[PDB]
Amino acid sequence: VKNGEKWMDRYEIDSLIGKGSFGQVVKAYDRVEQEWVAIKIIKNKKAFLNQAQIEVRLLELMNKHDTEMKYYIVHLKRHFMFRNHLCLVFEMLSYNLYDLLRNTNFRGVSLNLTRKFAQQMCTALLFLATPELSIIHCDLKPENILLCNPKRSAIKIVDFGSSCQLGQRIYQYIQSRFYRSPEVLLGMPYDLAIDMWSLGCILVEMHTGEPLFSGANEVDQMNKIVEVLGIPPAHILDQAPKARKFFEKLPDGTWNLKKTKDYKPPGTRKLHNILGVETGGPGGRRAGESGHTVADYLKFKDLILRMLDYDPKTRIQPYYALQHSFFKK
Ligand SMILES: Cn1cnc2ccc(-c3cc(N)nc(N)c3)cc21
Ligand SMILES: [Cl-]
Ligand SMILES: [Cl-]
Image (tube, rainbow, N blue to C red; front, side, top):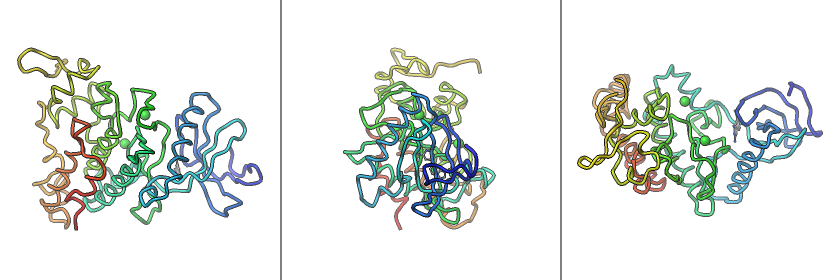
């Protein structure tokens, strides 16, 4: 697709904004509404088309529920078929939270800005947890959270390409590795709690600048999690189909790691130190900055650890996250 190209007496293609496995996204001028739009053009291949059809049904499903909380999700304006490609038309948005991290030279944004992102994302998750919706994003990460305007801190989630309703799971290998939940790593059946896990991983990374758990593969990933959170509870591992990819069961001291050729011991890389709760924030770089008091850090550490609960049934849901002391006055 070239700049200038006109479609159906209606769309004037300008440029490529984004590319994907799914196809590509372009900045186009809508001649009818008299405004710029983002067009997500799916490749004319069964695989992407079928997955894109599910994205469109889930977005259309969301647009049917007018309430406060639906406005944290990219608005699908319309979709249509053209030159044998499915095309999704969305409102134009700005750069994503990865680029934002890139721009801070991976030094991270303030606890104050992290909080504003956190509250918006928790609100999105509460909206998707609507019983008649019950949508699991399955690919929450900085790159899939966009700024609404480059001047401002308003954010919106994008890419429902992997999304599925509760009990419409297709693939068991889902989520970006860095943001993959234990349950999905362990090959267990997954609910909306995996997005909360991802959100935990994301918020820490927005403030520190570096991923919380940057596994180079699933075995690596699980060890970097164990470094911070220790061994997962017996009852979770007893039920896990891929427990034995990572751990070994014995009679006494039921569960332990499968050591390879050599990370820190289980639960020793304390989140306390990762955050720099008592040491002036990440790399001490927040020493004496306001809204970076130890009281402020500890509230965040609590909320994050509630988000990184190993147990998805006791892991903090979105409603109770919004009512946390981290979001008070
Ligand atoms: C880069 N960019 C600017 N405005 C946008 C609006 C939407 C999208 C977009 C939405 C969905 N559902 N999936 C992908 N992969 C991209 C990207 C945008
Ligand atoms: Cl990333
Ligand atoms: Cl995925």
